[PDB]
Image (cartoon, each protein chain N blue to C red):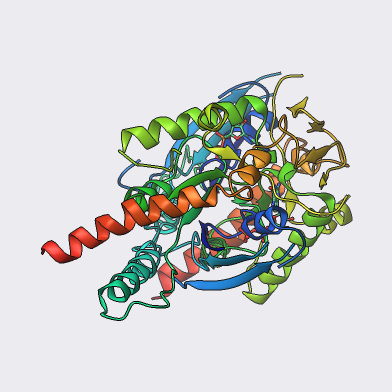
Length: 235
Length: 232
Ligand SMILES: Nc1nc2c(ncn2[C@@H]2O[C@H](COP(=O)(O)OP(=O)(O)O)[C@@H](O)[C@H]2O)c(=O)[nH]1
Ligand SMILES: Nc1nc2c(ncn2[C@@H]2O[C@H](COP(=O)(O)OP(=O)(O)O)[C@@H](O)[C@H]2O)c(=O)[nH]1
């Protein structure tokens, strides 16, 4: 079972920490770059190509910093299109990005111009799961208000983001990534990762491992790839 | 007693909250708001920078700040050049609070570009905004990483006493109500030395340490501007 997961976000949002917490243990100029690392998990076979975006914030300039992401995604769509167009399609590789994790910087306030510009330009090319990075920065009052402010700005700009009722209620997911003994040690308290009262991490962790990836795999193949196919052949 | 304090930083770093905690109760473009405090007279013009992050583009987003600071230097220069200098106003920015986004890692290209371009025009106090985001281990490592990158790029931050130099740059948390922030696991106190460097910053202003900042701006920053604009 192969799966391609992309992570896009400003540097220092706990992106790499989240990956290490989702899957146990550890793992510039001129911008922007597109890199990938593969992870094999055995128990059951799991091929996991993780697409990093060594941009991205990050900061000045940032003009068309979404483009290298767009180029990579459409490149893999082009590869799949040319693969099934050949007379001898036998051993076909599938390197299309099934899922994309976008890390929104708190706070907050609303979505920053960069968050709007990326999501509005990538929502029809990849499955986007918006995440409030470093969720332990926000109080329960702020976290709730930040979610509603994001969701209203998503609807306003016509952005199409990707037990089911519990998922829609807590969108976008506020997440905290951590290691050791599991959470983060502050001199006043400890923020637990596997807690529902603390994080939406368990909601995200469940949304991947127990083969919800297959749903993401189907949407990418049936919607995102097919829209690319219809566009590049008509004109 | 008049004082001009500037605050520069990316939106959503708790800048406004810090001002409200430094001075009690509630409160690219360049805007300013005046605050009068009575007990002792305190005229406080707070220069906001409604930029700034924030994001794309950001090219020359430091320029409107530079333009404002040099404009006030120009006003002071033309004031003391006139034959009848009687009631002279002093609107020069005595201090600037720059909010560094955690984390961290090091300083972002924007943090470098601003500080290296404003350190000789204004007194810069670097601050690690929203300090409750970092653990004591991360907070200590983030400080050292910043200070080494300050020295590497030849940035001259306001360096004034031993307790102040030890904790540079100051990691601060701004809050209100009953004083700190309410998390479902713990509470981060503002007036605590174990938690914040807020008390170090609060003390560095209220008890007339502002007069030192006022002297450095007048004797160094303004005089360097004066020597530059007249020699050429
Ligand atoms: N407050 C907070 N800090 C975090 C979180 N995750 C990671 N960090 C810390 O942030 C720093 C940078 O994390 P990193 O994963 O490298 O960020 P990235 O470069 O965007 O992937 C590290 O010192 C982490 O300990 C989080 O969920 N909340
Ligand atoms: N974690 C944390 N949050 C803060 C802090 N200061 C303010 N906030 C929160 O961040 C949000 C934005 O703060 P604000 O002062 O408007 O940021 P500004 O735009 O940079 O001035 C508010 O909801 C505050 O409750 C802080 O020191 N730490």
